[PDB]
Image: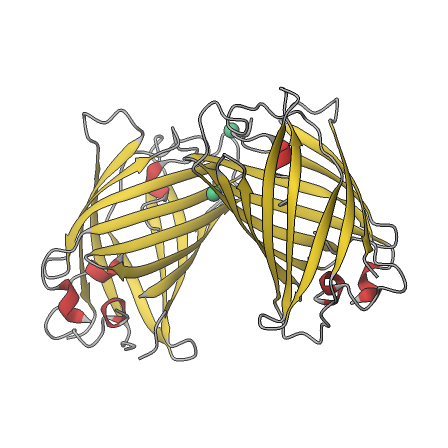
Length: 219
Length: 222
Ligand SMILES: [Cu+2]
Ligand SMILES: [Cu+2]
């Protein structure tokens, strides 16, 4: 399973989005290696301007996260190889995201097909009002093991920067389970870093992504 | 599950829709009498004007409220699955794009829900569908139902007649498969059919793109 991430692997990402009766779709193309922990993706909104700000959709392909030589026994995301990634995103004082995504290989490209449903967001609120900065800070992904579902649970809170100077908290609860039968880890975490940019020659509503993710927690 | 449909039951309907790179969603609320075969629903396009004329969606947006007479109470697959069943369809529009449909129909307390997804493929620009050349009308149709021992469910085949502004007719071939969700004591039926009648109206005080529905469907063949 690990041997598939030895080098560059092309990425395909599709997102089915439904928030407060607004339907949108996002295509994601790019590359990424797990030896460095790098991701380079360009997301395109093929349905005009998004009804929600980009940074909220960032959180919803860990498998390209770098696991050091002494932690290679703890990468569920690679052992699967696919898995499904379910999430619930609690935006504080704001709506919520339910997310289900299948992540498997399709030949050369690694594919992440997503469906999300946004419920009870506030009009002229921080999300539906696009009062979010085009930013993203660094975060930790606290990962534990789940023997009951042969998978993994994880908890973290994302800090979205607001235009006024305050901070938005999007509490994330996620569950992952393998698709095919056939390695759960100990309590570790994934340190993440992210830059949001744009292609100056794309007229479509888009987002360029650069990520660096590594693991830690085990000496 | 006959006892559940004794009287009036509230209905909830949602349609996840994608047709030729265009996105839409539709909410449906209403009631239904299975003792009569009556349905009264009001659908709302929460996304604004659909990229597709309503009458092509009427077929895919709950065949449990159909009236099966007292001598046909052994042939209602739909009522008996209520856990619910999964209704899958493929709608071939003649000389036009097609529809692929999936839906889950189950009870969530008082109301009955169908959660539906659909994908539209290979439709023509300035066609009858994408060009909105269909009259806001509908005709009467028969639903021939057969048994599926292998998948423990049923199938159905029929062709829908959509009226065109030309005075012509746009055909839509429907193929469907139903399979129970929970392990069912549900009995399968002999070859029979449902006679359907639909009326599409508008709520005068609603500004959103919408459609009001009235349906009378009863079972026959025995
Ligand atoms: Cu709006
Ligand atoms: Cu959709």
